[PDB]
Amino acid sequence: GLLCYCRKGHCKRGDRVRGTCGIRFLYCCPRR
Image (cartoon, rainbow, N blue to C red; front, side):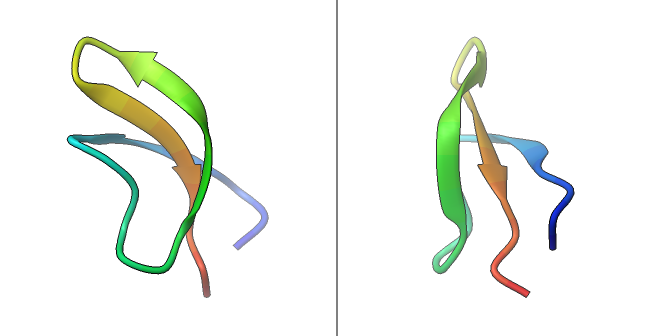
């Protein structure tokens, strides 16, 4: 998906990392 989301720990096993989101949260974009 074009829309990226925030996720704790790390991105989904297949997503694309963008950067950091917050305390123990990373900003990534969904594979599908």
